[PDB]
Structure formats: structure tokens, C-alpha cells
Amino acid sequence: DKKSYAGLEDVFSDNKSISPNDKYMLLVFGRNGCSYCERFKKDLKNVKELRDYIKEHFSAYYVNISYSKEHDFKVGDKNNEKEIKMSTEELAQIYAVQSTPTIVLSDKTGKTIYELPGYMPSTQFLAVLEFIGDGKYQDTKDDEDLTKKLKAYIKYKTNLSK
């Protein structure tokens, strides 16, 4: 049920239909009773810079693995895209979800750029979204390079909140 993220319907689109829609994609996997999922949602609610940025740059979906829905999952290139109807369990599985909240950030074709498996405080989390949303991930050479550049960028944004 959508009561999972009551009050955040301005951020999360209905997860019956999951795709980037000419935006970066943000997938949040959560569940009932997880204190980290609860803190993550308060940050989305109460940090305006975060809330605005997500709404500006991402198609965001909240998948509660406490339940089992079906999802039309549409990803891929302009010329060739695949739409598959799959269950909550099948969706979680393709992203190897094993803790909550797991956050998946993907490009406009639904190719995974980065995955975070845990709650991150809002200052750092916003820096991760910016790196992706402003396209800075593109100026990298591999996974080792993207990670170093990401970790550098988070530190800089951390210094910036003083």
C-alpha cells in the first residue's frame, strides 16, 4: 500500500509503472518497521533542498518489500526498450536487495549508475544525487574512478555545510 510513504506522494510516483521517463531514476527499497527507512523518509520530508532536488531531477519510486505487488518495469535505449511485468520479489532480486533501505540510482535509460545499501544522512545523500543528477558521473573512467570522484565530491559538500 501507498501508506508506506504517506505525505511523500509529491516525490514518489506510483510504482505500478517503473521507468526513468526522460529523468534519472531513483529506486528506494524499504520495508515496514525498519528504523532506517523511517529516518530516510523524514529527511525526504524535512530537508527542502533534498526534496526539491529529487523532484527536479529524478523519477522516484518507493518499493515496500513487506508486500507483493506487480510492477511494469520499463528500461532501455530510445531505440530499444523492454517493459516487463514483474513482482516486488523479482524486482528486489534483480537489484540483489538484502538490507534496507537500498537506494538505486540509474540513468535516463535505466542503466544502473550507483547503489547505496543503507541510510545516509541528508548532506551526504544530496551530494550523491547531485553527482548523478548534474551528470558528473560521466567524467569518469571506471567504477574505481567514479567511486573516488564520488567520495571526493561528498567530502567537499560536507565542508560546504559550515
Image (tube, rainbow, N blue to C red):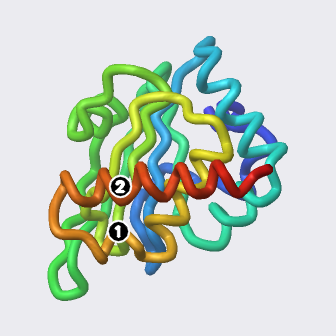
Q: Position of residue 80 (x, y in %)?
A: 15, 80
Q: Disc 2 to disc 1, how far (Cα)?
A: 27 Å
Q: Amino acid at mark 1?
A: Tyr
Task: Tell me the number on the disc at residue 151.
Answer: none
Q: Residue 35's x, y, as percent?
A: 64, 15
Residue of label 1: 137
Is 96 rendered above or below residue 125?
above
Q: Position of residue 92 (x, y in %)?
A: 31, 33
Task: Report which residue position mark 2 lands on.
Answer: 72
Q: Which residue sits at x=30%, y=51%?
A: 147
- Say which of 51 and 2 sits in front: 51
Left or right: 103 as drawn, with respect to 34:
left
Given residues 29 and 145, the one toward you in this image is 145
Q: Quadrant of residue 48?
A: bottom right
Q: What residue is at 49 percent from the left and 41 percent from the top? A: 28
Within 10 angstroms of label 2, few (less than 14), some, or many (20 or more) residues?
Answer: some
Q: Residues within 10 Å of mark 1 (few under 14, many from 20)?
A: many
